[PDB]
Amino acid sequence: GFESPRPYKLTHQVVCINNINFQRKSVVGFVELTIFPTVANLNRIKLNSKQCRIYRVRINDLEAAFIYNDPTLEVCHSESKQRNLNYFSNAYAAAVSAVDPDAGNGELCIKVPSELWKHVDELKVLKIHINFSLDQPKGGLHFVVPSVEGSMAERGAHVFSCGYQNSTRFWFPCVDSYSELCTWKLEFTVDAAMVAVSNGDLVETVYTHDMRKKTFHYMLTIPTAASNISLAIGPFEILVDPYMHEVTHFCLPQLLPLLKHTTSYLHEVFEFYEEILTCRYPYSCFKTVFIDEAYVEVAAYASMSIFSTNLLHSAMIIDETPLTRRCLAQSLAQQFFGCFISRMSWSDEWVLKGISGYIYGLWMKKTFGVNEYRHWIKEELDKIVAYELKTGGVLLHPIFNPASHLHFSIKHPHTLSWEYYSMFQCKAHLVMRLIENRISMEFMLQVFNKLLSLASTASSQKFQSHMWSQMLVSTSGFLKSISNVSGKDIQPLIKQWVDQSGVVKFYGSFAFNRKRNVLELEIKQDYTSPGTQKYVGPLKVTVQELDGSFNHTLQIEENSLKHDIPCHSKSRRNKKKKIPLMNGEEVDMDLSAMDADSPLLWIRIDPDMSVLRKVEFEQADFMWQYQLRYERDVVAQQESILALEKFPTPASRLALTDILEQEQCFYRVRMSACFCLAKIANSMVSTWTGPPAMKSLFTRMFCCKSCPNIVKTNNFMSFQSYFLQKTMPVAMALLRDVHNLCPKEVLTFILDLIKYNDNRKNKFSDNYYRAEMIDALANSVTPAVSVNNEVRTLDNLNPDVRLILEEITRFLNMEKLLPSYRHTITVSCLRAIRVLQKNGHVPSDPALFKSYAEYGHFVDIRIAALEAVVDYTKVDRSYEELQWLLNMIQNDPVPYVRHKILNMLTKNPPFTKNMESPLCNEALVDQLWKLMNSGTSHDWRLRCGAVDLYFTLFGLSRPSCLP
Amino acid sequence: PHELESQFILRLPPEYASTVRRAVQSGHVNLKDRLTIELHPDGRHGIVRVDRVPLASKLVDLPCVMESLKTIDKKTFYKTADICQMLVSTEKKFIWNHGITLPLKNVRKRRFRKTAKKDVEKEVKRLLSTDAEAVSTRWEIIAED
Amino acid sequence: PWNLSNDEYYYPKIIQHSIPAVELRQPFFPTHMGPIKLRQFHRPPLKKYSFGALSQPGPHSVQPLLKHIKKKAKMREQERQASGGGEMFFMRTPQDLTGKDGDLILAEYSEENGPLMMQVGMATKIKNYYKRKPGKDPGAPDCKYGETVYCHTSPFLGSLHPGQLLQAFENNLFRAPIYLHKMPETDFLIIRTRQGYYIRELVDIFVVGQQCPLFEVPGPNSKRANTHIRDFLQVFIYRLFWKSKDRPRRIRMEDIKKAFPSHSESSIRKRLKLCADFKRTGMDSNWWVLKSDFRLPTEEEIRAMVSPEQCCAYYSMIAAEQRLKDAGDDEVRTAPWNTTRAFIAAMKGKCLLEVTGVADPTGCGEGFSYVKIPNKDADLRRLSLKNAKQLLRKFGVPEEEIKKLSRWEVIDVVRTMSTERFSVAEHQERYKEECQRIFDLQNKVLSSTEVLST
């Protein structure tokens, strides 16, 4: 049951936009809302509006009086001397709650005229006509106007609606909540050479009487919220999908072949999401818009998605196909379960984010294989356990503070830190995988189909929300639908992993009792760490003995420590028979390293990742080597690679080398075995016999049979030896000698890989392989032996580093004349120049990176150069570079770059709270408090980034370096 | 508490079976008055009265075991009861040799292993009671006499 | 840009009972079965009521059900369409397991005492295995009940013919071939309760062939057997503690002694020693209160303790124990622990089974027996080929053997006509052919609609 927090119900909204002026960055328009009051004596009506100048408001064609105030413009007063962050977080939460449409509130308060009170008490319709104007919007809707001359279509100027969550208040007045569903009528009067893309279906396109402008009329009969309404106006090249004909793809001019190749996969994503769920795609059209200077890499609205143009690749670009493919896939998953089925509160957001991430993981499983699915699930689980042990924990479904261990309030999406938002979505889809583990996948897809079917029977009624609230899901409704389809309720699993905000830590060690033939496990939990919680459920453990692989369920109550499980025979060591594996197959194992008295080959605690856990198991090194070689699970091979770094014995070198030589191993395991072999090789110097690690293996796999030092000409058509070939010198360059100087045998090998590179014969580009070669050249740089702080000149230039510097100069200059993809070689060469500057080789001068961080460059070059400037101002304690970065945060045209500068200055801070630095003035405290209070008031993501930066630099209490 | 339901099979003469079948498929409560069942305190004898016409009945034991299986989707079937008795209408006499289906005929005689088969205990108990009651007991395994 | 997961090297290639069944509730799953109740195992006699409407002697009207069945079916369809229209789970109460509603079929068994048998409240599925014809095939002959699956590898001992559909009961306990027959025209189904008689017609009755056991019945007093015994007692004790209304939760010992009367009270004390303590005086006197530090296990943990199929295997063991005990080594081989061990070992390929033997539940050539077997010239020289070839055409030997004109072969053949190394392939082939022939004969005998003379 859904009861509105608003005293009115909104039925229909007309959004008309005229006069989109690109020179002056200005729109004019009106908005006409059709509300039905649910309570008599409605009097004031409270709507949401930011940055719009409200000209006049007429209610039922009668002139009404409005008052506007935004408490989130300046959160605390300018003349308050408070400088602690808990004060700002409480004031910011109160300010966002005072404009919240999820309460009854709002920023624009319109007073109903007196003569309509007899029209409002007996509950009859009210039609509110506001007309407004955006004069020059800061972060409302982004105007990308290039400075080439010509007409606005000839120079490539466009507008798009940017922002996250409820940010539609930034460009027209609305009820900007996800729970106020209404039908829509959208008119946009644009230039005749431009096209206006929006939500709904385009019913017509009429000309103006001078035929210089045309009006696009859109209609949206599926009741969506105001927060799902978008807009993209530009000189877009239109491409109808040749497979599905209601899907149109819009790109920027001159990028039509890239659009043709890139969006050619999307019909398979549509077919997948419509056959695992049994509902068809709910909207009547689908539109993909590719734009410049995007807010996020992929945004999903109702019947529309806005991607950045940096996803567009051609047919000869690999290492970008899978990333763009999965961006399209998660946009479509959010089309199904973020835009059609919406949220009922700010709680129950974990339901929608979990269903979106879970069905996108099912797509990844079918498309890229179960092994890529397991690797992705393991990397997300490692991400969450790192974040939750780092700071507190992520609390899905809080109850309204519920989480007081962090520095922000979790009551609203616009007060969350961006890393918390990312980890929120990550934990939501892993908890949905856990619900699939308890209640099987076909029942899970039946739950999702029942939600979609209730929403689509709701979506066709005309009753103003008598039935339109069946399109809003809640937690209680989701659990009730689960209990309807399965008969089991998941309330212990919901109580543990949703309502409780923690992950578990397992420390395991075993001992084999030879007398009674048992395996005595010893599993203890660390439940006193700040991020942890105590697990009391069951726990699966998989033991591989000589007779095969056996699963055991252990009951781990609070007082439990020793778990005795039984062991089988050892009669497959009496005769040589094959040892049967986890799957149905069996292999020949070399049992010379195994103990004579124990049959068990390896043990895995929680193999299926059925809890949110971090396992620290103490096996013997031969058990880790057997688990690396003969396991049929990629997460166990990865964890054995990760645990073999502590055992540098030559049997582990043989194990990793046999993994590296082995095709029919998953390629991301071999790419990890490269770096593990490099670390082991660095640890057993003065024992290593022959050549450096992986060199003979590289010449055996990727070089000519007649010439060992000449590499084969590039043929990248295998896509697994391409990735292994481009990752093996990067790990080979980490080879550390006894003198701590990289062997001139590996550096010469990398330089010969660079010289003899011929790419005139493959059908794929070479930009990522050459960029990884520059990364391998940067990995070989050891710190220089400066004497008496000698000024770095050409007289003291290392003879090794002169070759590296010549190569990166040649590569960067050739990129200036012939570029590649993603400007990968510019990014790699800027990263390598920063590596050479971090050691004492090149003079520590930020002027090159400051010239590459200007506005007109590509955004990857910009963020690489700004990462170099952030690293410089951390190491050299530069005041003027920090003022340069803070000025660039305040006034840069691209807001993604501002968010990225705040993000990088949070990750690599110039000082922490423990450090005494010269940069801890009262002036810097006043600048960052002014940046939290004012200055970042227009983005909701810069303000949370400024809160994160103030927390990283000065902590939760009063800045110490202050009177 | 819950008591397991006790289902049995009723076999009628063919004309009376046709009248009872027509009245069941009709569905009125008129059938309730027409069809009655009186079970005698023997436990293995009865009257079934169809349209107030008395028929003589015997409750017999069936050689196989049947099980009623209900369903809602015709793909998963839930066992509801075990049937082992039939009230045919027209000890060794109360045992039915044939099964209900056509392939199962003379099942007890032909399709049943005699190893499983083979009252004896009750006779042994009576003999033990007589021995306990007696003062002196004399026993000999005998020959032909 | 592709799969790139070497999946063929890492990975080279369901039954939901009712909530009374998975919770092991005591009408459906009895705690104790005496000797007269073990002799009447799965053959429950018609009990006389002491109180009720049928307890009074006299004629009793039956009540035909037609409005109740269609009202309950319409109500369940409303429940399913209100819950989103998918497939639902309905058997949540004991009153859902009545015969008064839903589409009933009957299932007759060919064997007298099967090795495994379902209790009341447990679910089973009907799978229609259909082997396609070589090359083109029209499609599975459609069937009213069950779902169709295309089986290249025969589930049963024999192998399916091309174009042959075979229905089968499939659950966790066994898998057995079933054969749909129409009901007799005279038989109806009377459901008697305490209140009155109710009548349904039946139209579908299956005949269930010889079961292929998927669960191993334990032996008497075996480790698994006595483990189930103490687990069944622990689950009953936990569910009595959950049913207790006083705080802290307290039970009485003679409730457990009423449920398990064959148990020595030392074993019951042993189960109550951990998780309870005896109060002899003051409040809670002569009660076993629950310990305050003891967390009583949740419903899913108690369900994970004992499975219903383990209870069916235990009931099969104790019923066979009674039948063997009443009948004073051939019979011991026919005991279900031996036959279930033999069949499951044959399915892993450990050993082979003599398909003709004494464990045969028919007592004739039909049906299998599941007991383990291990997997394992002076005058002939004078002819000197020339005259031996003439002897072969004089012996009417076919011209192929005469034609090969071999030495050893021609003479071995003429010695054989004058009469008229390995042990793995030939024995395995003979066992497989015998099993297939037995399966075909059983199917022909079972699906026959031919009338058999009394």
Image (spheres, coloured by chain):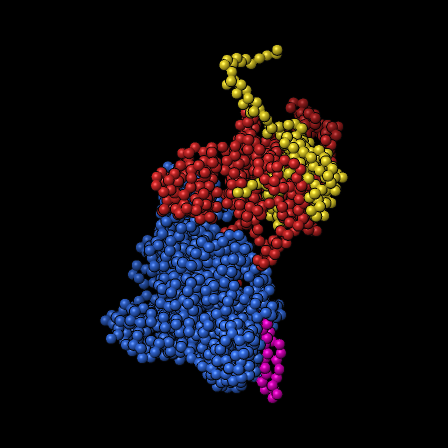
Chain colours: A blue, B yellow, C red
Residue A143 percent coordinates (x, y): 48, 80
The relative height of residue C19 versus residue C256 in the rendered view (above or below) is: below
Answer with the quarter of the image where residue A676 lies.
bottom left
Residue drawn 44% across the image and 48% down it:
C298
Is any part of residue C376 visible from this angle?
no
Residue at image coords 53%, 72%: A38
Asked whether, in this view, residue C373 is left or right of residue A818, the answer is right
Image quarter of residue A243:
bottom right
Q: Is residue C301 left or right of residue A116?
A: left
Judging depth in this view, the residue of C197 and A637 nearest the camera is C197
The rendered magenta stretch, by its main secondary structure, is classed as strand
**Residue at the extreme left:** A788
Q: Position of residue C53 (x, y in %)?
A: 61, 40
**Place of residue C78 in the rendered image (x, y in percent of width and height, measured from the top left):** 61, 56
For the record, the magenta segment spans A199-222
Question: Image point 47% across, 63% down: which residue?
Answer: A348
Image position of A579 with respect to A733: above or below: above
In this orientation, does residue B41 appear? yes
